[PDB]
Image (cartoon, coloured by chain):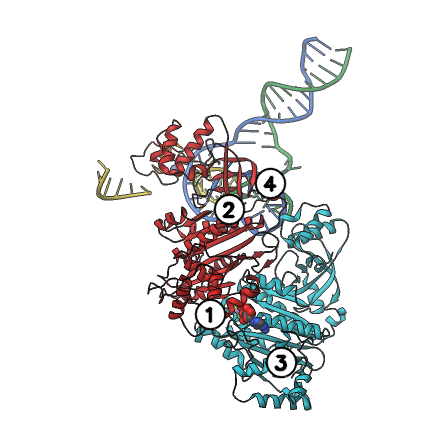
Chain colours: A orange, B red, C cyan, D green, E blue, F yellow
Amino acid sequence: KPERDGLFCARIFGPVKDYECLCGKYKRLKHRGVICEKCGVEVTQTKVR
Amino acid sequence: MNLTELKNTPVSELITLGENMGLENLARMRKQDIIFAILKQHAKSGEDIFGDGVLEILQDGFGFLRSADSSYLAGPDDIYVSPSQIRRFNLRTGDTISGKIRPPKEGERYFALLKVNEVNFDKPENARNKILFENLTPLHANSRLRMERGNGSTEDLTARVLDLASPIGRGQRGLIVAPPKAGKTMLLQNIAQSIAYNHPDCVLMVLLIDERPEEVTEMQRLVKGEVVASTFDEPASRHVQVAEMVIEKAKRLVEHKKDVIILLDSITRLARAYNTVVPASGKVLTGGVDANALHRPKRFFGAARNVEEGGSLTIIATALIDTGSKMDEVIYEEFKGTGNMELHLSRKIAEKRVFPAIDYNRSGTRKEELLTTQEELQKMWILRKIIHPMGEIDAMEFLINKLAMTKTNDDFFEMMK
Amino acid sequence: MNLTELKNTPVSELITLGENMGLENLARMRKQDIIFAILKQHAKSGEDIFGDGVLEILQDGFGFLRSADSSYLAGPDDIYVSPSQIRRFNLRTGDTISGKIRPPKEGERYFALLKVNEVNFDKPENARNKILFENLTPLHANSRLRMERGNGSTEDLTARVLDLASPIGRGQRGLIVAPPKAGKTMLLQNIAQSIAYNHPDCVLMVLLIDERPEEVTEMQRLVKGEVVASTFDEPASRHVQVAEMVIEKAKRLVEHKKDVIILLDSITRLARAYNTVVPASGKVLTGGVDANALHRPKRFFGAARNVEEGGSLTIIATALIDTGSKMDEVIYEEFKGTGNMELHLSRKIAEKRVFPAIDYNRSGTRKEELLTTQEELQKMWILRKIIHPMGEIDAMEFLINKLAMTKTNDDFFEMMK
DNA sequence: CGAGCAGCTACTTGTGAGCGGATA
DNA sequence: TATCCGCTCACAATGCCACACGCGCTGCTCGGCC
RNA sequence: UUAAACCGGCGUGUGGC
Ligand SMILES: Nc1ncnc2c1ncn2[C@@H]1O[C@H](COP(=O)(O)OP(=O)(O)O)[C@@H](O)[C@H]1O
Ligand code: BEF
Ligand SMILES: [Mg+2]
Ligand SMILES: [Zn+2]
């Protein structure tokens, strides 16, 4: 998985998977558009990256 | 402000406090998150925080400060410490680091410790002027610690029994061998209350492994000192985590020339937890254990030793037998020869509601002359000799009877004569 | 400079020494690291070091020099030796190589031995002019070694008991069969102190296996010679490591025509350790042992032999019985017929506080005429005959009484008549 | 513990412009 | 101080297709935020 | 809120038109 603040990252660029966060806490469609409690990434498609 | 001053307060009190501080009602988050948000708000107010935490190092390099009420576990109230302090003072695991802390910004998770103020209730120079644990000379138990309460109560029985069977000293390694349903937990409570009420000069620290949550609550608010527990709501990983926490804390406190008593119950449960956490090595011995899966428990039971130069480390640990399985029996085999203090609780007398059910036959003390004086040993030996006429059941009768008529040791000795 | 001259000094003294040498305060690293850094600094000063270490070879080819206070273990103070010296002198395991050493640079870990100076307190030509251990002729014990101290003390009892029951000679193989709680460790201390105070001409070397750290400290500073111990803080691998260290050291010292006495306690513990370190062979015999898992212990107990051409190797080893398990019983079976000296300690007399609890019935000596002269055997035989009227308990009474009234062997013999 | 950082190529040809340059 | 003259560097050199290949071991240093 | 399905970038060499 990407580093916290390395070259590859999620909270800086976007989720590495479509509608799936890095921690797997938010994975359904209801949480689409909200950030998690530690990484704080807007869960969405990979195109954002 | 500080951690324990908020953690020894209940959850409703913390919710009311956070709502009084003008915050989003914190009755929705856990108590640890409540205190975390309260500290974040207090730091937002324009000031620093003064925190305290016991120290943990992983293979990364920085330090984690776990709190007391968290049972030394992972949580948001654990303080971050940059590895620079570890490179400076070589702070190993087991410091109640007390110092100034600041709130974490974005990209961070925990509070960062700015400067050191208190190193195990000592000056930070003790962090650079002290002796390690592996280098000193372990000795036998010199000091004698009385167990009897002194009120003539019905549970005083247990204490005085032990006092006339095998006393307890600083630096001892006590192992209790008892089948299920023998009165273990109330024995722990009785002996802890007696050692803490009769001798407040010595420090107590009780360990609970795989008990019920009601047992945790009954243990935590009843005995003095820190009450660390690790129940089933955490896996064997967090079991070994809290175990290594408390052992390194005791080691460092002993290095600080302090008397540390560790109650532990039971050893078979932590041995199973360790077997769970250590991978296999291709071979399985009797009972289903590994080769190195015994090295952790061995070390854990043998860390006890008497420090003649200052401080001491005594442990009182119970074991599980008559469980039907094999691994518990081999564990008892391995740990019955490594301890310098062995005691046994019977089950046949226990199920007859005749308590306490001490095995006066298999009870023993390693090098008891350093724990018992001239005529003291005279009295103890002649009573052992007169109880020696082969007896378990009516031997317990004689003991409990002559113990219920009398109040102190000298009363029994001078009335039996 | 040298190793033992710094290792027999305490840890605080070494810390003060390293701080006096102008160094980073070494109270943060272990004592072995303290001495390592002190040697590195002394070598940085512009000079060489003169070190000493007992030799170990693995399947690699080079040599490791383990130190005395390290209990012959792996550590930074172990000196590296290039295999060239092994190809030159064929230095097998068990040389206290004493020689010149230089500090290690980057890419290295330990000091490198430049040249040989002392080979087991002998000229390096003895490294090329000597005889191996497997080639000489093992014989029976010729010399007689008195055990009684000669002060009439209360522990002299034990010694004189053995002296009138079964004496000890050079090249003997003694096995003590004793249940738990029979007075083993103080017996070891008593007999070692007597052999080292009465006969300083013979060399002592005591082995401790699976004892308490306080027992290690009480053994290490009380008896003469090297006190090697291997407690539970090391796994069975390091157990067998130190065991093979000491056995090859004794073998080489005997090859150097020296008298080497090896105290060992107990054998069942090292047998369990070996069973732990040897893999299975698909089959498990009685007690849970393997086929080849007995070959190591067998060899280890049978390395004892009397060298009639020069030097001797005697062993005094204790065994564990009445442990409830089977493997200890089969181990005792295997080792009760392989020894050339058998003695037994009773537990029923021991728990009556009547010490020492010798089994005068099962005590014996292989070919005792080579250990006892004409009228000497006359006296011993007639006393055995008069004690022969079936007795354990009041037999111990008679022995201890007639032994407490008297001071030496001849006094007892000429007062009983 | 991870990751990295690193020690362990060479007779083009032209066409063009920018930059000395030197020299009275 | 103008006016070429020449030195020196940037920039370039068809399009596709097909196939194959290798883009490493180990000592040292640094990072200090599960 | 519930059910079903899914989750070649570079360089080199060679050869051909
Ligand atoms: N020679 C002796 N004289 C007096 N007391 C003894 C003697 N030998 C043993 N004992 C007693 O027997 C006990 C044996 O101690 P311990 O080390 O627990 O058992 P063991 O030595 O058999 O392992 C000691 O507490 C000691 O008081
Ligand atoms: F010290 Be006992 F013999 F284990
Ligand atoms: Mg012993
Ligand atoms: Zn997340």
Badges 1 and 2: C-beta atoms under 8 Å apart?
Answer: no
Q: Is residue A11 above or below residue C348?
A: above
Q: Is residue B289 visible?
A: no
Residue wearing tag 2? B58
In the figure, is residue E16 to the left or right of C369? left
Residue wearing tag 4? B123
Q: Give the chain letter at badge 3.
A: C
Q: CA distance from mark 4 to mark 1?
A: 54 Å
Q: Give the chain letter at badge 2.
A: B
In the figure, is residue C194 to the left or right of B406? right
**Classed neighbour count for the residue bearing mark 2: other residues with Cα under 10 Å, few (<14), some (14–19), many (≥20):** few
At x 72% / y 67%, what residue is drawn?
Answer: C88
Q: CA distance from mark 4 to mark 2?
A: 25 Å
Provide residue B30's location: percent of width, then percent of height: 37, 38
Amino acid type at image mark 3: Leu
Amino acid type at image mark 1: Ala
- Asked if badge 4 and badge 2 are on a common chain, one would say yes
Q: Is residue D4 above or below residue C78?
A: above
Q: Secondary structure at mark 2?
A: loop
At x 66% / y 57%, what residue is drawn?
Answer: C77
Residue B239 falls within the magenta-colored stretch: no
Q: CA distance from mark 1 to mark 3?
A: 51 Å
Magenta stretch, main secondary structure, is: loop
Which mark is first along the chain, 2 or 4? Answer: 2
- Asked if badge 2 and badge 3 are on a common chain, one would say no
Instruction: Indicate if the residue with disc 4 has its beta carbon within 8 Å of ligand 1.
Output: no
Residue wearing tag 3? C403
The boundaries of the magenta stretch are: C351-361
Is label 4 or label 1 in front? 4
**Classed neighbour count for the residue bearing mark 4: other residues with Cα under 10 Å, few (<14), some (14–19), many (≥20):** few
Is label 1 or label 2 in front? 2
Residue wearing tag 1? C280
